[PDB]
Image (cartoon, coloured by chain):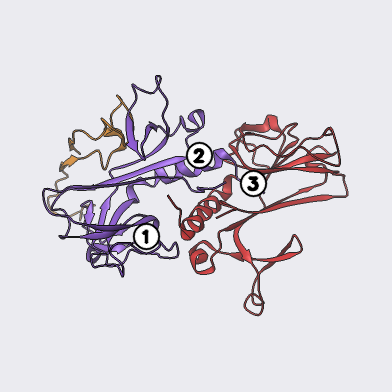
Chain colours: A purple, B red, C orange
Amino acid sequence: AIATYNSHVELAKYLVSKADSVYLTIGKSTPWSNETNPPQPDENATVLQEVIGYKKATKVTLVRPSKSPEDDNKNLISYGNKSWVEVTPENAKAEGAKWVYLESSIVGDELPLGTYRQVGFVMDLVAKSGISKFNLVPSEVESTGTLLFFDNKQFQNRSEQTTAKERFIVEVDPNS
Amino acid sequence: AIATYNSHVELAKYLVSKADSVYLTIGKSTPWSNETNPPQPDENATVLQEVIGYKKATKVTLVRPSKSPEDDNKNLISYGNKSWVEVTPENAKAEGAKWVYLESSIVGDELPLGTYRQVGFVMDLVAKSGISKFNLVPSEVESTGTLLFFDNKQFQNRSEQTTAKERFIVEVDPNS
Amino acid sequence: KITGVGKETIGIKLTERIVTPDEDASLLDQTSGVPSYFSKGADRLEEK
C-alpha cells in the first residue's frame, strides 16, 4: 500500500531535525578512470572514495518551488534555473514542503588542499571526544555515521581564496 | 537528486522508533457506491472517513522477505501468501530490511462492532489524561497524531466471537 | 559532605562560560526562526 504526500513531508521534517549530525563530505582527490566523464553514483556505496574529510552542513531546511508575487519578499534560494523558498517545520503541511535543501561551504583553508571529485552529505557523524570543530578529516571522526546523498564531480580544484559551495535539493522518494 | 538504499533503511528505523505512538484505525462503516469496487485511496486524506476508533499497534518492526535455510533459525510471519522474517534496528543495514511491518488486533467489541471498509495506521496519537487502554473511540483521544498509511478495502464484519487482526507490509519508497 | 572533625567551611564556587547558538537553538533569530538566514548571531557569557 501507498505512502502519502504528507508522509514525505514528515520524513523531511525528521531529516531537518537531524541537522546537527549532517556533514558535507568531499573525496576522490585522485583521477577517475575517465576524468572527462566520472563513473555512476552507486547507491550501495556507504562512503566516498579517497575521503578528504567532512564539514557540518551550513543550511538544512524544508523548501518548495517559489511563486511570484507573493513569495518575492521571503528568504529565496536559486537552484537548477528555479527559485525556491525556505519553509519552517510547523508550516510544512500548510505549504506542502516535501523537499529538503542541504548546503555547506568549505571556507578556504579549513581542510587539506587541492582537488575533489566526490561530494555528499552523511548524517550521524560522531567525532572523537574533545573535538568540536565543524570541519573534520577522517582521522578525527569516531563514527562516520551514514552516507545519505551524494554525487560524482569533475576536475575542478580548491585553494585558499576559492571557498567552494556545495548543495542539493532532494526528497526521500524522488519518484512516487 | 537520489536517496541511497541505506537511507530508506534508516527512515524505516525512524518509523520503528515511533512505534510507541502507533495506532491502527478502522472506518468507512457505511457502503461505497459499488461494494464490489471501492474508490481508489487518496493520499491527501489526513484521517479515515467514518472513524470507528483506534487500537495501539501490537507489532511494529523491520522485516524482510524470508528464505531457506538461513531464516529457518528465526521468527517467521505469514502474510500475502509470502513468508516474512523479523529484523532488529542495529541489524537493519546488514539484513537490507527497508520494509516495515505493522499489525494490530481488535478482540470482540472493545471497539463498537459492525462493518469497516477503511484500514489505516497513525503515529503521534495521544489520549486524554489517564486513558491508558489500547482501544479508543475518537472522543477519548486528545490528539489524532498523523495517518501514515491506509487502504479502501471491500467490507468486512467484526463480531463478539472475532478478533480482527489487520496488518500492512510497507516501505517508505515502494518504487525505487 | 564533611568529616565531622576540626574546622569545616562550606562555600559556593561560580564558574563562567561563553555559550554559542550552535549549543543553543534559542540563540537563533526570531526575525526568521531556527537555523535559518538572519539566525546564527551572538554568543553569551553565563555564570553558575
Residue linked to disc 1:
A145
Residue type pointed to by label 3: Ile
Q: Residue at x 71, y 43 (%)?
A: B151
Q: Residue at x 45, y 40 (%)?
A: A99
Chain ID of residue with mark 2: A
Mark 1 or 3, nearer chain start: 3
Instruction: Using the rendered image of the protein, determine whether residue B38 is visible from the camera's viewpoint.
Output: yes
Instruction: Using the rendered image of the protein, determine whether residue A124 is visible from the camera's viewpoint.
Output: no
B20 to B83, vertically: above or below = above
Secondary element under disc 2, as helix, strand or loop, is helix
Circles 1 and 3: CB atoms closer than 8 Å: no
Residue A2: mark? 3
Q: Residue furthest top?
A: A69
Residue type pointed to by label 1: Gly
Q: Would residue C42 appear left or right of B64 to someone viewing this image? A: left
Chain ID of residue with mark 3: A
B3 to C41, vertically: above or below = below
Q: Nearer the viewer, residue B46 or A31?
A: A31
Residue linked to disc 2:
A9
How many other residues sit within 10 Å of disc 1, few (<14), some (14-19) or many (≥20)? Answer: some
A148 to B33, vertically: above or below = below
Q: Using the numbered discs, state the Cα–Cα distance from disc 2 to disc 3 in whole angstroms.
A: 14 Å
Query: Which percent across, then down, holds residue A23?
Result: 31, 52
Residue A11: mark? none
Mark 1 or 2, nearer chain start: 2
Chain ID of residue with mark 1: A
Q: Nearer the viewer, mark 1 or mark 2?
A: 2
Q: Nearer the viewer, residue B67 or B138?
A: B67
Q: Residue at x 64, y 74 (%)?
A: B71
